[PDB]
Image: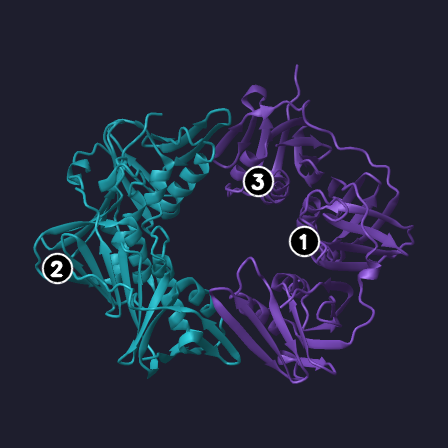
Chain colours: A cyan, B purple
Amino acid sequence: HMLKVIVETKTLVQALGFASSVVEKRNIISELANIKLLAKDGLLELSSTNMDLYLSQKIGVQVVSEGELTVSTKTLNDIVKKLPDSELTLTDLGTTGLEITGKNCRFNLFTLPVESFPVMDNINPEASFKISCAEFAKIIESTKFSVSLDETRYNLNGIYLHVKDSEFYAASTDGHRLSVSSVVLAEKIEDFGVILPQKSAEEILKIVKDSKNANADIEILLSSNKIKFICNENVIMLSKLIDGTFPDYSSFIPENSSSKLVINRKIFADTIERIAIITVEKFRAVKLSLSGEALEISAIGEARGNAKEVINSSKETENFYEYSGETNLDIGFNPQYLEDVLKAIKSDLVELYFSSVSAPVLIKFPESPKDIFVVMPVKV
Amino acid sequence: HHHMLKVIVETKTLVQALGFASSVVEANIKLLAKDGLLELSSTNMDLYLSQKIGVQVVSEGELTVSTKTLNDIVKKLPDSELTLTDLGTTGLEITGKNCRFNLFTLPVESFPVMDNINPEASFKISCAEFAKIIESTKFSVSLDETRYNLNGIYLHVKDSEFYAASTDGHRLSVSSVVLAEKIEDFGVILPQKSAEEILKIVKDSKNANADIEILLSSNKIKFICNENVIMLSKLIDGTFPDYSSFIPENSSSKLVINRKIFADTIERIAIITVEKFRAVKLSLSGEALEISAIGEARGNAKEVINSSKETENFYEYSGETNLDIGFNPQYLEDVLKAIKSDLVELYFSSVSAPVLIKFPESPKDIFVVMPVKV
């Protein structure tokens, strides 16, 4: 009936960090602030939910006595991440509550009855496939920054996850830019797509980036109302889906490109950032003045001043600049939208493909051919 | 004709100075190029800051410019040197190896001048000595803005010794250094914001090794940090109480404990408490100390520190009887984190009387903390 386990403190801290992000108090059911602990079969199962997402983590423990309880997530998390012992002992003492002991310390935390705590929903998958955790992290990091934050563009406030011809794609757009990243699947699988809520994207990303699971694989199960992640077997996350229609973004991608810029990624990013300081929120734009000889990045800010920096031709890697264009091109962009892309891929060079002053740029990284980025320009 | 400013400056030295100007205005900064030096001036409602940095002066002149905009642009320039040039209507132009920035200027006539001071007390101490007395007292200033006699730091000289002291009605903190030159008595109340600003200045790696001159008047105080940095501050209009009677003279029991162990344990035990009732219970006996705490609808917590004469885990309590006494954990933490010391001593009386906290390594730092019911 009553739980008693001995647990590795570092492993409980990691799990409590993941459970902490889940519990957001938009919902009146106060039991959902708690985390449920199930000791059984040599494992401690930790369950967290906010009614939109459900997280289940199984960690190895020494099970002295099996049992289950619920306890405040924040209170348990705040106490455990300040204990220096390598191991702790969790013991349920009934009316006292959950007792936590290390060498020479004792904490008692009131519990709540487990009967009302929800169990994870079922999923009846229409598509299932496995990719590596590092591969999943890449496509999420390549797309999370261009999700819309406009609550009225409801179908654009997530990450479109879809399989087309056995290739798994993530895509995001906000009406001003598009980001796509894909990995080829090893097994043939039929087409299916879902829209992942942004909060679920951020939670699963922290989980797959963890050093324990980096190097491992993640199983992704898709249905029409739910998505399920099984990350390194022990961590299971079930999420609801955004009920909407992701737009056909294939037509946003420019197929006819007149101009081509190849430039050192860091220099381009550093120069865009330092020039953008002068701008104001009401007009966030930098001007790229492109010619074969050099690029002039400039910007104006009302009642503050102006700024300009010149990048000259160089075949040297550290300062690379090459612009192959039939005509010279003067085109503007939101500096933030270029910066998001340039900081997404750790690469030496970056390529930009231009056409008209009102047509979007295609940004590619010759090291990462599966990452596609399109940014609309602005009048400058 | 006209008159335009032009200077060539080492980027790192302008960055350091602009950092001090930024903290002041959180509102433009005035630039005065003259006699091979760049004077930068910043002000708020309590203080006036003037820093002069060594520059190559091409053409003398004066201007005012947005502090934040200048600071934000300069700390992103990689060049070793920049050239600032006043083009009038264009504004201040900043140039690096391949960049040019233009910032609009504001009239220099509207910029305030530093007040004069007719000092009644003048003396020099080391910057490390001044940083110590401020860090030992800055955390226990009152936050009742209308209680003028207590919401600054009492800086005063008595019998050739310079003291800082602060209280909030719940604790008292004092720190002093013996002066080298004979000086008559004088006292002032330093605004908390001015204390924080001069502390950042004296702690900076440039000045940390240097000396600070402190000039006291009845309505203003002036700091001369490393000859190069001059700060004028307004004063709090009140009279600090005679705290000499606050120091407990009759103490029954004495606790000696490892400082780090003591602080870490109080902190981990205090986690269970709620904001409305921040209290930890020190249950003291010769055999051990039990630190406990309660949090309504949260639970409880306890940790035991046993007798030991070894430094890393030192605990000794000299008490005929056991003593159970409570404290706001934060007020103990403020004192324990103020002095980097191996051990700490606490002197007790009754469960309702204050504790006297001393650091045998730092005998010029004195702390008194009132208890709470537990």
> Which quarter of the figure has residue A311?
top left
Label 3 CA crowd tier, 10 Å (few <14, some 14–19, many 20+):
some
Q: Which residue is the site of mark 3?
A: B81
Residue A179 visible, this orientation: no
Q: Nearer the viewer, residue B321 or B199?
A: B321
Q: Which residue is the site of mark 2?
A: A125
Give the secondary structure at mark 2.
loop
- Are labels 1 and 3 on one chain? yes
Label 3 sits on what residue type?
A: Glu
Label 2 sits on what residue type?
A: Pro
Residue that lies at the very extreme toward the top in this rendered image: B1
Label 1 sits on what residue type?
A: Lys
Mark closer to the chain start, 1 or 3 = 3
Cα separation between marks 2 and 3: 63 Å
Which of discs 2 and 1 lies nearer the camera? The answer is 2
- Are labels 2 and 3 on one chain? no
Give me the chain letter of mark 1: B
Label 1 CA crowd tier, 10 Å (few <14, some 14–19, many 20+):
some
Q: Nearer the viewer, residue B122 or A116?
A: A116
Q: Position of residue B282 (x, y in %)?
A: 63, 73
Give me the chain letter of mark 3: B
Classify the position of the C terminus of chain B by image quarter. bottom right
- Are labels 2 and 1 on one chain? no
Cα separation between marks 1 and 3: 25 Å
Give the secondary structure at mark 3.
strand
> Which quarter of the figure has residue B106?
top right
Q: Nearer the viewer, residue B81 or B111?
A: B111
Q: Which residue is the site of mark 1?
A: B203
Label 2 CA crowd tier, 10 Å (few <14, some 14–19, many 20+):
some
